[PDB]
Image (cartoon, rainbow, N blue to C red):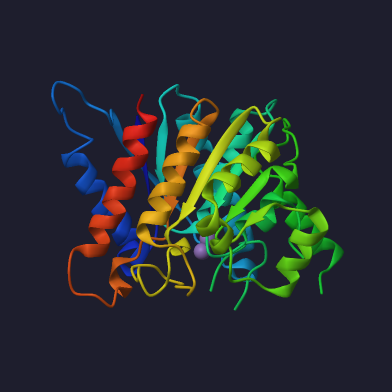
Length: 301
Ligand SMILES: [Mn+2]
Ligand SMILES: [Mn+2]
C-alpha cells in the first residue's frame, strides 16, 4: 500500500489540517508503516506538496502549480499497482488529485463515493468546490473568465478522459448546502443518501449505490470526517449537526469497502484538524486512526 500525505508548499505550519496529516503519517508509520508479524502493509510514505486555490487571488498560480506539480506527482502514484491511501489534508485538494486519477484511467468510467456533510459543488462563504470543478458546474463571469475556468476544470484531461457521469457520483450524509448546489443536484439527478436514510437502512443505501454504480469500471472513495455529527466529532474545520455517529460511519465504511472491494482503486480521507477540537483528550485522534485501520485492513488484501 502507498500512503500519500499532502502538505502545503507554503505556510503548512499555519494550517490545522496539515498538522492533522503529519500526526496521522507519524502514527501510521509506527504501525501499518512498519513490519508487523513479518509484513509491511505501507511500503511507501510519499509527501506531496500543494498550493491553496484562492480563486481570483491566485488563479493562474494555482493553475500552473496543479498542471506542473500536483497532478504530475499524483499521476505517478496512481500509475503504480499498489493501493493508495491519500491524506488530502483539505477537501479542496480532491480536485487536483482526482484529475490525476482520471488522467491515469482515461478510458475508464469512474464512480465516486463521496462521504461528506457538504456537496462541495459551489464555494460557500467555509468549503471549496472540488466537485463543482470536476462536474464543470463552476457557476457574473467574463468570456475570458469562463475560458480560464474551462482551462482549469480541464487539467489533466487534454489527451482526454471521459466526462464524469453525474449519476455515478454518490453523496453520503450531505446536509449543509447552498440552494445553488441543491439546484445542480436536482438538475443532474445526483444520488444523495442522507444521514437518516443511512441510519434507517444502511443495507438499502448500499444496494441502491450498487445500482447507480453498476456500469462504472473503477471507483474512487473520498471521505470527509465532517460527515460525523458536529457535536460528536470536533476535530474538523466545518462541523455540521445531525451527522453520523462514529459507529455508523464505521459500519457504512465497512460495507462500502466490502461491496466495492474489486473496483475501488483509491481512498481519500480528509479534513482532520486537531487544532480546532474542543475536547482535551485522545478520543478523536483515536477515532480517526481507527477509521484508517479499518480502511487499511480491508484494502490491503
Ligand atoms: Mn468536503
Ligand atoms: Mn465537508
